[PDB]
Image 1: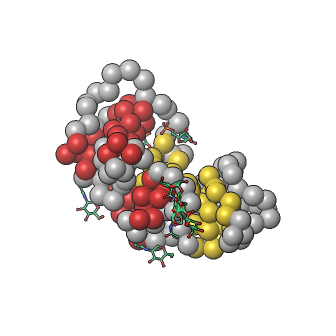
Image 2 (image 1 turned 30 degrees about the vertical axis):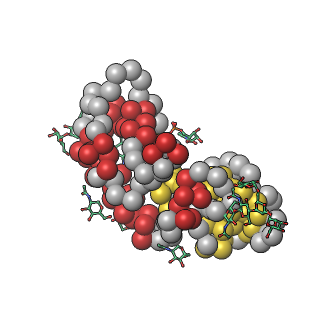
Image 3 (image 1 turned 90 degrees about the vertical axis):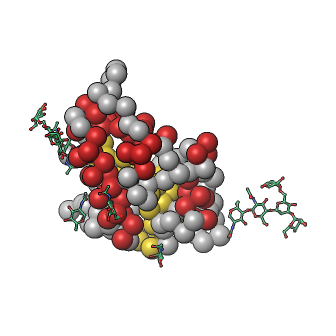
Length: 161
Ligand SMILES: *[C@@H]1O[C@H](CO)[C@@H](O[C@@H]2O[C@H](CO)[C@@H](O[C@@H]3O[C@H](CO[C@@H]4O[C@H](CO)[C@@H](O)[C@H](O)[C@@H]4O)[C@@H](O)[C@H](O[C@H]4O[C@H](CO)[C@@H](O)[C@H](O)[C@@H]4O)[C@@H]3O)[C@H](O)[C@H]2NC(C)=O)[C@H](O)[C@H]1NC(C)=O
Ligand SMILES: *[C@@H]1O[C@H](CO)[C@@H](O[C@@H]2O[C@H](CO)[C@@H](O[C@@H]3O[C@H](CO[C@@H]4O[C@H](CO)[C@@H](O)[C@H](O)[C@@H]4O)[C@@H](O)[C@H](O[C@H]4O[C@H](CO)[C@@H](O)[C@H](O)[C@@H]4O)[C@@H]3O)[C@H](O)[C@H]2NC(C)=O)[C@H](O)[C@H]1NC(C)=O
Ligand SMILES: Nc1ccn([C@@H]2O[C@H](COP(=O)(O)O)[C@@H](O)[C@H]2O)c(=O)n1
Ligand SMILES: *[C@@H]1O[C@H](CO)[C@@H](O)[C@H](O)[C@H]1NC(C)=O
Ligand SMILES: *[C@@H]1O[C@H](CO)[C@@H](O)[C@H](O)[C@H]1NC(C)=O
Ligand SMILES: *[C@@H]1O[C@H](CO)[C@@H](O)[C@H](O)[C@H]1NC(C)=O
């Protein structure tokens, strides 16, 4: 039901992807998205101390030099509070999800966004998720590179019949 999405290293893409490449980080959690989007005043303001407890998750913002906590806070505000009700189980889930992502190639990994690299003739995956979705910037007929891992299709598991 919830979509889990993350960023992948790519020196060819400006921002978080380049920062991950430079720091030797392969996968950085973006969010865990239930169907319901939060609106209005959050029930708790996420502190830097709470958000720093999501170990390994890099901020997408250049303002924090891709560390913490703009992306982390935006995720709690837009997807967290109204669905998890309390910050503690949300931090634990996000931390465990990132800990799992840091181990290597997840059991379910599907391309979201690509940067086609002419030199290697590969779709370099910049964002991926745990379920298939329509692709962005991925050139048809080309193999996929998920933080170095070569996959023939957009997912590391068969989707179709
Ligand atoms: C990781 O990804 C980044 C971005 O793609 C790469 O950085 C690029 O690397 C190249 C090669 O060193 C750099 O190209 C050189 O750019 C010089 C100037 O271009 C502008 O300069 C600014 C700063 O003002 C850069 O930040 C901008 O990108 C600008 O466009 C240019 O002078 C230079 O030419 C000289 O060297 C070449 C090649 O040797 C000679 O042929 C040429 O005649 C001249 O002497 C280069 O073309 C490029 O600037 C870098 N871009 C950024 C954004 O930092 C890394 O190389 C990639 N890393 C890997 C694989 O580790
Ligand atoms: C997918 O995403 C959903 C969110 O959409 C996740 O479900 C939420 O999971 C958390 C558990 O991590 C649940 O939070 C706990 O909620 C308790 C309140 O629950 C009531 O029951 C129903 C649902 O059965 C709610 O919809 C109601 O509105 C109620 O409010 C709450 O009491 C509890 O807090 C207790 O424990 C914590 C520590 O764990 C203490 O800090 C706290 O004070 C208190 O003692 C939790 O906050 C939450 O209910 C779930 N939300 C929904 C809407 O179902 C799924 O886990 C996700 N799954 C995956 C696989 O990602
Ligand atoms: N259900 C969702 C939620 C977010 N997203 C993606 O993540 C980006 C950031 O969305 P959020 O600001 O809601 O985290 C969106 O512009 C989109 O690229 C998505 O594709 N599907
Ligand atoms: C982390 O992976 C382990 C092993 O697959 C699993 O039991 C657990 O559900 C995972 N946690 C999250 C938050 O995905
Ligand atoms: C988060 O994950 C790490 C592994 O990366 C773990 O051992 C750490 O103690 C966890 N943090 C919390 C706040 O549970
Ligand atoms: C990143 O992924 C590549 C491809 O699997 C791997 O060889 C390398 O060890 C990984 N680095 C980290 C820090 O996990």
